[PDB]
Image: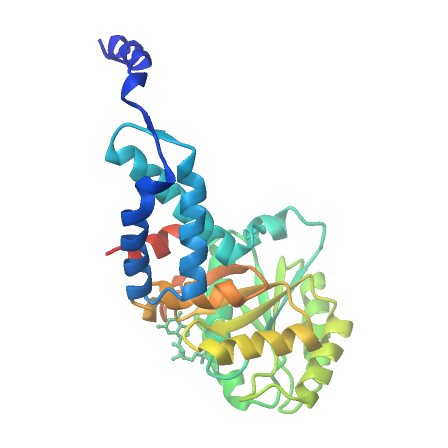
Length: 297
Ligand SMILES: Nc1nc2c(ncn2[C@@H]2O[C@H](COP(=O)(O)OP(=O)(O)O)[C@@H](O)[C@H]2O)c(=O)[nH]1
């Protein structure tokens, strides 16, 4: 008798009321209050509310749950547009649906942003996806980074290619790529020179690594908490090197959700993964659900 109730459900159209702009006034102001409370910036708040008006005005609803369902689907869609720019995001399918014999990934970013840690996370995830990997340590003058990757490479049971201190960073990356060909390794991950500040020497070296290593995907690593410094790092790597995608680290330290969402709005490249902790598994695909849960209670 549950199919008899579903047939009855076809004849329930009289309770369906069309939403008028005037109907939205109060709830739009309450959503605004909560967004701003949850550290959502003004521009993102305005975009999100405008997308809510546009997705609601046409519609017919008969109860609060139907309204909530349009609101939630609209929120998840706006958040998706903010973070990914509606670009493809799955690195595994990127690698798998690609022709490249070893798939070469290069990583950019300044010091203390979490770059060596999320390379270990990327290694961890590709292992969980049955993809073999090696790391090329091409930050050859920051001997600290050499230690960090050496620990991770050992814990993760993965080969680390490294040179002498101060070695040609393009050699480390080139050698790692031939090593990966010879051993039929699926993916190469190249660490690049982390500094306190981008500068002219770093740019020339990155471009030399790029033209000699020929990577298939370039990822910038940004601290989701660093605000305008993060936007300044992204703009300088954009103008002088170019990259394809962003990984935001420390998103777990953004309690209310809006800080990383407000940063992403001003980024021009998609955010493809998010670091959410210090452990290897603390790497999640972009998820609108993450931001909806944090922003709203
Ligand atoms: N809470 C949190 N901490 C992180 C995350 N990613 C990195 N960190 C921490 O940030 C600090 C610096 O990271 P590290 O990989 O050494 O940065 P690097 O110098 O750029 O290579 C470390 O203590 C990391 O544990 C994250 O997603 N969440």
